[PDB]
Length: 341
Ligand code: NI
Image 1: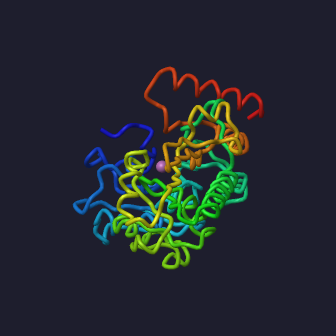
Image 2 (image 1 turned 135 degrees about the vertical axis):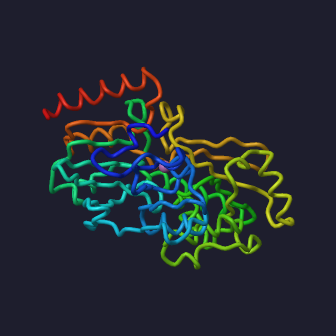
Protein backbone atom coordinates (compact mmCIF):
# COMPACT_ATOMS: atom_id res chain seq x y z
CA UNK A 1 0.00 0.00 0.00
CA UNK A 2 0.92 3.59 -0.92
CA UNK A 3 2.66 5.60 1.85
CA UNK A 4 1.43 9.04 3.08
CA UNK A 5 4.31 11.15 1.70
CA UNK A 6 3.29 10.07 -1.91
CA UNK A 7 -0.25 11.40 -1.57
CA UNK A 8 -1.37 14.94 -2.30
CA UNK A 9 -4.18 15.90 0.19
CA UNK A 10 -7.32 17.40 -1.20
CA UNK A 11 -6.69 15.99 -4.70
CA UNK A 12 -7.05 12.74 -6.59
CA UNK A 13 -3.25 12.84 -7.18
CA UNK A 14 -0.17 10.71 -6.30
CA UNK A 15 3.52 11.26 -7.08
CA UNK A 16 5.96 8.44 -8.00
CA UNK A 17 3.44 5.75 -6.86
CA UNK A 18 3.24 2.97 -9.48
CA UNK A 19 4.33 -0.09 -7.36
CA UNK A 20 1.23 -0.37 -5.16
CA UNK A 21 -1.38 -1.52 -7.74
CA UNK A 22 -4.56 0.61 -7.98
CA UNK A 23 -4.39 3.44 -5.39
CA UNK A 24 -7.84 4.12 -3.77
CA UNK A 25 -9.23 7.30 -5.35
CA UNK A 26 -6.28 8.20 -7.61
CA UNK A 27 -7.51 9.87 -10.77
CA UNK A 28 -4.03 11.02 -12.01
CA UNK A 29 -0.55 9.57 -11.36
CA UNK A 30 2.37 12.04 -11.64
CA UNK A 31 5.91 10.85 -12.46
CA UNK A 32 8.74 13.28 -11.62
CA UNK A 33 11.51 11.51 -13.62
CA UNK A 34 12.60 8.26 -15.36
CA UNK A 35 14.60 6.60 -12.56
CA UNK A 36 13.67 3.00 -11.64
CA UNK A 37 12.90 3.54 -7.91
CA UNK A 38 10.34 6.17 -9.05
CA UNK A 39 8.72 4.49 -12.10
CA UNK A 40 8.65 1.01 -10.33
CA UNK A 41 5.48 -0.69 -11.61
CA UNK A 42 4.76 1.00 -14.98
CA UNK A 43 4.39 -1.17 -18.20
CA UNK A 44 2.32 -1.58 -21.42
CA UNK A 45 -0.58 -2.83 -19.25
CA UNK A 46 -1.00 0.44 -17.29
CA UNK A 47 -4.42 2.07 -17.91
CA UNK A 48 -4.53 5.25 -15.74
CA UNK A 49 -3.50 8.80 -16.81
CA UNK A 50 0.21 9.55 -16.32
CA UNK A 51 1.33 13.21 -16.11
CA UNK A 52 5.04 14.00 -16.68
CA UNK A 53 7.49 16.03 -18.87
CA UNK A 54 7.81 15.53 -22.72
CA UNK A 55 11.15 13.75 -22.20
CA UNK A 56 9.77 11.38 -19.51
CA UNK A 57 6.88 10.70 -21.90
CA UNK A 58 9.31 9.69 -24.70
CA UNK A 59 10.97 7.15 -22.32
CA UNK A 60 7.60 5.71 -21.12
CA UNK A 61 6.44 5.15 -24.72
CA UNK A 62 9.69 3.75 -26.26
CA UNK A 63 11.41 2.03 -23.30
CA UNK A 64 8.43 0.82 -21.25
CA UNK A 65 5.83 0.58 -24.14
CA UNK A 66 3.17 2.43 -22.15
CA UNK A 67 0.37 3.15 -24.57
CA UNK A 68 0.14 6.63 -25.99
CA UNK A 69 -3.46 7.28 -24.85
CA UNK A 70 -2.40 7.27 -21.17
CA UNK A 71 0.71 9.57 -21.60
CA UNK A 72 -0.04 13.21 -20.76
CA UNK A 73 3.07 15.36 -21.34
CA UNK A 74 3.06 18.98 -19.92
CA UNK A 75 5.30 21.88 -20.94
CA UNK A 76 7.48 23.51 -18.25
CA UNK A 77 7.00 26.96 -16.64
CA UNK A 78 3.31 26.94 -17.72
CA UNK A 79 0.10 27.04 -15.67
CA UNK A 80 -1.97 23.87 -16.59
CA UNK A 81 -5.33 22.63 -15.24
CA UNK A 82 -5.47 18.90 -14.48
CA UNK A 83 -8.75 17.37 -13.14
CA UNK A 84 -9.83 20.86 -12.04
CA UNK A 85 -6.59 21.78 -10.19
CA UNK A 86 -3.86 24.26 -11.33
CA UNK A 87 -0.34 22.73 -11.60
CA UNK A 88 3.09 23.89 -12.91
CA UNK A 89 6.14 21.72 -13.75
CA UNK A 90 9.61 23.20 -13.08
CA UNK A 91 13.07 21.92 -14.06
CA UNK A 92 14.58 19.93 -11.18
CA UNK A 93 18.28 20.16 -12.26
CA UNK A 94 18.48 16.36 -11.79
CA UNK A 95 18.54 14.04 -14.93
CA UNK A 96 16.96 14.79 -18.38
CA UNK A 97 13.22 15.27 -18.10
CA UNK A 98 13.18 15.54 -14.22
CA UNK A 99 10.64 17.98 -12.73
CA UNK A 100 9.38 19.59 -9.55
CA UNK A 101 5.60 19.95 -9.35
CA UNK A 102 3.73 22.99 -7.89
CA UNK A 103 0.11 22.18 -6.90
CA UNK A 104 -2.40 25.04 -6.22
CA UNK A 105 -5.04 23.34 -3.96
CA UNK A 106 -8.73 24.36 -4.22
CA UNK A 107 -8.65 25.49 -0.52
CA UNK A 108 -5.75 28.06 -1.05
CA UNK A 109 -2.85 25.83 0.07
CA UNK A 110 0.21 25.72 -2.17
CA UNK A 111 2.40 22.49 -2.27
CA UNK A 112 5.88 22.09 -3.87
CA UNK A 113 7.10 18.48 -4.54
CA UNK A 114 10.76 18.59 -5.51
CA UNK A 115 11.05 15.05 -6.92
CA UNK A 116 14.79 14.42 -6.99
CA UNK A 117 16.64 17.79 -7.38
CA UNK A 118 19.96 19.63 -7.17
CA UNK A 119 19.03 22.99 -5.69
CA UNK A 120 20.43 26.05 -7.41
CA UNK A 121 20.23 29.87 -6.87
CA UNK A 122 18.60 30.11 -10.37
CA UNK A 123 15.47 28.51 -8.84
CA UNK A 124 14.99 31.68 -6.71
CA UNK A 125 14.00 33.34 -10.17
CA UNK A 126 11.56 30.75 -11.43
CA UNK A 127 7.78 31.01 -10.86
CA UNK A 128 8.55 30.16 -7.22
CA UNK A 129 9.45 33.85 -6.53
CA UNK A 130 5.85 34.98 -6.78
CA UNK A 131 4.25 33.27 -3.80
CA UNK A 132 4.07 31.36 -0.67
CA UNK A 133 4.47 27.62 -0.17
CA UNK A 134 2.74 25.95 2.78
CA UNK A 135 4.17 22.36 2.35
CA UNK A 136 7.47 21.25 0.84
CA UNK A 137 7.97 17.55 -0.05
CA UNK A 138 11.82 17.53 -0.11
CA UNK A 139 14.59 15.38 -1.69
CA UNK A 140 16.67 14.93 1.53
CA UNK A 141 19.27 12.44 0.00
CA UNK A 142 22.25 14.45 1.41
CA UNK A 143 20.67 16.24 4.42
CA UNK A 144 23.72 16.18 6.75
CA UNK A 145 26.73 18.57 6.81
CA UNK A 146 29.32 15.94 6.08
CA UNK A 147 27.92 15.72 2.53
CA UNK A 148 30.12 18.05 0.49
CA UNK A 149 31.13 17.78 -3.19
CA UNK A 150 32.27 20.23 -5.89
CA UNK A 151 30.22 21.87 -8.65
CA UNK A 152 29.35 19.79 -11.80
CA UNK A 153 31.43 22.34 -13.78
CA UNK A 154 34.62 21.63 -11.68
CA UNK A 155 34.15 17.89 -11.99
CA UNK A 156 33.74 18.17 -15.78
CA UNK A 157 36.85 20.41 -16.02
CA UNK A 158 38.85 17.68 -14.20
CA UNK A 159 37.52 14.90 -16.47
CA UNK A 160 38.19 16.79 -19.79
CA UNK A 161 41.77 17.72 -18.81
CA UNK A 162 42.54 14.20 -17.53
CA UNK A 163 41.26 12.56 -20.74
CA UNK A 164 42.88 15.11 -23.15
CA UNK A 165 46.27 14.80 -21.35
CA UNK A 166 46.27 10.98 -21.42
CA UNK A 167 45.27 10.58 -25.10
CA UNK A 168 47.71 13.29 -26.27
CA UNK A 169 50.52 11.41 -24.56
CA UNK A 170 49.23 8.12 -25.98
CA UNK A 171 47.12 8.27 -29.20
CA UNK A 172 46.49 4.55 -28.79
CA UNK A 173 44.58 4.91 -25.44
CA UNK A 174 40.79 4.17 -25.27
CA UNK A 175 38.48 6.05 -22.95
CA UNK A 176 35.62 4.17 -21.21
CA UNK A 177 32.74 5.76 -19.13
CA UNK A 178 30.28 3.74 -16.92
CA UNK A 179 26.49 4.23 -16.83
CA UNK A 180 23.40 2.48 -15.35
CA UNK A 181 20.51 4.93 -15.86
CA UNK A 182 19.85 8.32 -17.41
CA UNK A 183 21.59 11.36 -15.97
CA UNK A 184 25.27 12.50 -15.96
CA UNK A 185 25.46 12.51 -19.78
CA UNK A 186 27.74 15.59 -19.62
CA UNK A 187 30.63 13.35 -18.37
CA UNK A 188 30.90 11.32 -21.60
CA UNK A 189 29.70 14.12 -23.93
CA UNK A 190 32.30 16.63 -22.75
CA UNK A 191 35.14 14.03 -22.97
CA UNK A 192 34.13 12.95 -26.52
CA UNK A 193 33.90 16.57 -27.67
CA UNK A 194 37.47 17.44 -26.50
CA UNK A 195 38.80 14.30 -28.17
CA UNK A 196 36.98 14.93 -31.55
CA UNK A 197 35.09 11.61 -31.34
CA UNK A 198 31.51 10.34 -31.24
CA UNK A 199 30.52 8.27 -28.21
CA UNK A 200 30.11 4.55 -29.02
CA UNK A 201 27.53 2.40 -27.15
CA UNK A 202 25.07 -0.52 -27.35
CA UNK A 203 21.85 -0.38 -29.25
CA UNK A 204 19.80 -0.31 -26.02
CA UNK A 205 21.71 2.72 -24.65
CA UNK A 206 21.58 4.52 -28.06
CA UNK A 207 17.77 4.04 -27.99
CA UNK A 208 17.54 5.64 -24.48
CA UNK A 209 19.66 8.68 -25.55
CA UNK A 210 17.50 9.12 -28.67
CA UNK A 211 14.50 9.87 -26.29
CA UNK A 212 16.19 12.85 -24.57
CA UNK A 213 15.81 15.93 -26.86
CA UNK A 214 19.57 16.69 -26.73
CA UNK A 215 20.41 19.11 -29.58
CA UNK A 216 22.46 17.72 -32.49
CA UNK A 217 22.53 14.25 -30.83
CA UNK A 218 23.01 12.44 -34.16
CA UNK A 219 26.33 14.30 -34.44
CA UNK A 220 27.46 13.08 -30.95
CA UNK A 221 26.66 9.33 -30.54
CA UNK A 222 26.86 6.10 -32.52
CA UNK A 223 26.43 2.29 -32.41
CA UNK A 224 29.56 1.77 -34.55
CA UNK A 225 32.09 0.96 -31.84
CA UNK A 226 35.06 0.79 -34.24
CA UNK A 227 34.69 4.40 -35.30
CA UNK A 228 34.74 5.76 -31.70
CA UNK A 229 37.49 6.24 -29.09
CA UNK A 230 35.07 6.99 -26.20
CA UNK A 231 32.98 3.96 -25.27
CA UNK A 232 30.09 3.54 -22.77
CA UNK A 233 29.69 0.38 -20.82
CA UNK A 234 27.36 -0.68 -18.03
CA UNK A 235 28.67 0.44 -14.62
CA UNK A 236 29.14 -3.13 -13.36
CA UNK A 237 31.77 -3.73 -15.99
CA UNK A 238 33.95 -0.76 -14.83
CA UNK A 239 36.55 -2.98 -13.02
CA UNK A 240 39.93 -4.46 -13.96
CA UNK A 241 38.32 -7.73 -15.15
CA UNK A 242 35.54 -6.14 -17.17
CA UNK A 243 37.87 -3.66 -18.84
CA UNK A 244 40.57 -6.29 -19.75
CA UNK A 245 37.80 -8.28 -21.27
CA UNK A 246 36.58 -5.21 -23.23
CA UNK A 247 40.13 -4.36 -24.56
CA UNK A 248 40.49 -7.89 -26.00
CA UNK A 249 37.43 -7.18 -28.23
CA UNK A 250 38.83 -4.02 -29.82
CA UNK A 251 41.08 -5.96 -32.29
CA UNK A 252 44.51 -4.55 -31.27
CA UNK A 253 43.47 -0.94 -31.90
CA UNK A 254 44.34 0.17 -28.33
CA UNK A 255 47.08 -0.59 -25.73
CA UNK A 256 45.70 1.32 -22.72
CA UNK A 257 42.33 2.15 -21.03
CA UNK A 258 41.45 5.15 -19.05
CA UNK A 259 37.99 4.73 -17.41
CA UNK A 260 35.63 6.92 -15.42
CA UNK A 261 33.05 5.82 -12.80
CA UNK A 262 30.76 8.62 -11.92
CA UNK A 263 29.42 8.13 -8.37
CA UNK A 264 27.50 10.25 -5.95
CA UNK A 265 29.23 11.28 -2.72
CA UNK A 266 31.83 8.80 -1.30
CA UNK A 267 33.86 9.21 2.04
CA UNK A 268 37.05 10.16 0.13
CA UNK A 269 35.22 13.58 -0.33
CA UNK A 270 35.81 14.06 3.45
CA UNK A 271 39.60 14.37 2.83
CA UNK A 272 40.58 14.80 -0.86
CA UNK A 273 39.97 17.85 -3.16
CA UNK A 274 38.85 17.26 -6.73
CA UNK A 275 42.24 18.55 -7.99
CA UNK A 276 44.12 15.95 -5.88
CA UNK A 277 42.08 12.86 -7.04
CA UNK A 278 44.11 9.86 -8.22
CA UNK A 279 43.09 6.67 -9.98
CA UNK A 280 43.36 2.97 -9.20
CA UNK A 281 45.79 1.31 -11.60
CA UNK A 282 46.62 -2.27 -12.72
CA UNK A 283 48.99 -2.58 -15.69
CA UNK A 284 47.69 -0.65 -18.74
CA UNK A 285 44.23 0.07 -17.01
CA UNK A 286 43.42 3.12 -14.84
CA UNK A 287 39.98 3.83 -13.18
CA UNK A 288 38.96 7.25 -11.81
CA UNK A 289 35.99 7.61 -9.42
CA UNK A 290 34.54 11.07 -9.90
CA UNK A 291 31.91 12.73 -7.61
CA UNK A 292 29.41 14.02 -10.16
CA UNK A 293 26.21 14.63 -8.11
CA UNK A 294 22.66 15.27 -9.43
CA UNK A 295 21.33 15.78 -5.80
CA UNK A 296 21.71 18.95 -3.56
CA UNK A 297 24.72 19.23 -1.27
CA UNK A 298 23.77 19.97 2.36
CA UNK A 299 24.69 23.65 1.81
CA UNK A 300 22.66 23.99 -1.45
CA UNK A 301 19.62 22.33 0.21
CA UNK A 302 19.85 24.62 3.24
CA UNK A 303 20.13 27.69 1.03
CA UNK A 304 17.03 26.77 -0.98
CA UNK A 305 14.85 25.95 2.02
CA UNK A 306 15.91 29.16 3.93
CA UNK A 307 14.97 31.17 0.83
CA UNK A 308 11.57 29.41 0.27
CA UNK A 309 10.55 29.54 4.01
CA UNK A 310 7.97 26.72 3.89
CA UNK A 311 5.54 26.28 6.79
CA UNK A 312 6.01 22.52 6.92
CA UNK A 313 8.57 20.10 5.43
CA UNK A 314 7.88 16.40 4.54
CA UNK A 315 11.12 14.54 3.64
CA UNK A 316 10.91 11.91 0.78
CA UNK A 317 14.45 10.30 1.20
CA UNK A 318 16.01 8.58 4.33
CA UNK A 319 12.58 8.12 5.91
CA UNK A 320 12.92 4.53 7.08
CA UNK A 321 14.90 4.92 10.42
CA UNK A 322 14.10 6.81 13.62
CA UNK A 323 17.63 8.19 13.79
CA UNK A 324 17.41 9.56 10.17
CA UNK A 325 14.03 11.18 10.73
CA UNK A 326 15.22 12.74 14.03
CA UNK A 327 18.47 14.07 12.54
CA UNK A 328 16.55 15.74 9.66
CA UNK A 329 13.97 17.36 11.96
CA UNK A 330 16.79 18.91 14.03
CA UNK A 331 18.36 20.46 10.91
CA UNK A 332 15.02 21.87 9.75
CA UNK A 333 14.57 23.56 13.19
CA UNK A 334 18.03 25.11 13.15
CA UNK A 335 17.46 26.46 9.62
CA UNK A 336 14.10 27.95 10.73
CA UNK A 337 15.56 29.59 13.92
CA UNK A 338 18.58 30.96 12.07
CA UNK A 339 16.51 32.59 9.29
CA UNK A 340 13.54 33.60 11.51
CA UNK A 341 10.55 32.07 9.66
NI1 NI B 1 16.57 10.20 -9.34
